[PDB]
Amino acid sequence: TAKKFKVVTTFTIIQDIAQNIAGDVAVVESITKPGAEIHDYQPTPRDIVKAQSADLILWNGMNLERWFEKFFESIKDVPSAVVTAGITPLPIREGPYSGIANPHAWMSPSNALIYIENIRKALVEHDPAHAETYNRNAQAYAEKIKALDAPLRERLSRIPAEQRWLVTSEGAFSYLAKDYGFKEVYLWPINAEQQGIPQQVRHVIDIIRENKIPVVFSESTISDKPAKQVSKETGAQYGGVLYVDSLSGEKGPVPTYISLINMTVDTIAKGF
Ligand SMILES: [Zn+2]
Ligand SMILES: [Zn+2]
Ligand SMILES: [Zn+2]
Ligand SMILES: [Zn+2]
Ligand SMILES: [Zn+2]
Ligand SMILES: [Zn+2]
């Protein structure tokens, strides 16, 4: 037990999944901090030194981290791995990124099994002295993820099909909405600098008309104001905050990936 194998991830969700696979035999750190916007994060010099100190770097791919490839050019002799390998992307459906992969694949718990296997495989490949701990921890964590499916569906089972509309600010929930039979509506399709600020807001306020959607949400790394506005101009309650792009701090409501899924579904459910 000298200095432990060091893994650096781009953001907090991957950090928590990887630390569950690593257990005590490896140290997993995230480049972005809890609460920080991850799509257009601007790396600092201290971020370079952190990534350069790693034995292995994990990132999402599906162009989630618009900043990563340019950043990674400053890192030498450190292998990286894309943890969404083998996931089939859902395309973005409107706006200037229409047709690009929707990168929020981790919001489907069945996809998280694929994240887990990609991370396990990378850990075993580059740290083979601990292949037994990594292989045991991954199987145990995959079983925790599989166990979520029944309580999650049961928690949402009081909402009838026609009523299952999920109205959020970022369209970050397409993978979760597909898994649990929700229709998605959103103020913008993916976080970015962009136009369409008030026109999608009026188009969303539209769809809330004929479907009498009762509740709309925001998310933890972006401004809650546009959702709160939509709630004002309609009769819909503001139900947010949902979690997708970041965990909370270790003492906050959402310190782990499992707590992020459970609490996001729980908040949708109570919103209805
Ligand atoms: Zn050891
Ligand atoms: Zn080691
Ligand atoms: Zn490798
Ligand atoms: Zn043993
Ligand atoms: Zn739309
Ligand atoms: Zn996002």
Image (spheres, rainbow, N blue to C red):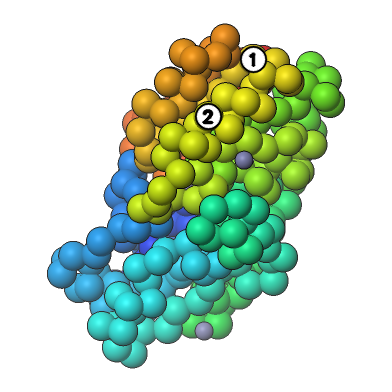
Residue 136 seen in render: no
Name the residue at the bottom extreme.
77
Circle 1 packing at 10 Å, graded few (<14), some (14-19), many (20+), is: some
Numbered circle sitting on residue 214: 1
Q: In this view, does 249 lie above or below 156?
A: below
Disc 1 residue type (three-letter): Pro
Q: Where is residue 3 in the image (x, y as percent from the top left)?
A: 29, 72
Q: In this view, does 10 lie above or below 73?
A: above
Judge left or right: residue 101 versus residue 210: left
Q: Position of residue 39 (x, y in %)?
A: 40, 57
In which quadrant is the N terminus drawn? Answer: bottom left
Point 76% across, 43% down: residue: 179
Name the residue at the top extreme.
235
Name the residue at the left extreme.
45
Q: Position of residue 117 (x, y in %)?
A: 65, 66
Point 66% across, 27% down: residue: 207
Q: Earlier in the sequence, mark 2 or mark 1?
A: 2
Q: Position of residue 178 (x, y in %)?
A: 75, 44
> Which residue lies under the disc numbered 2?
202
Q: Is residue 89 above or below residue 54?
A: above
Disc 2 residue type (three-letter): Arg
Secondary element at image label 2: helix
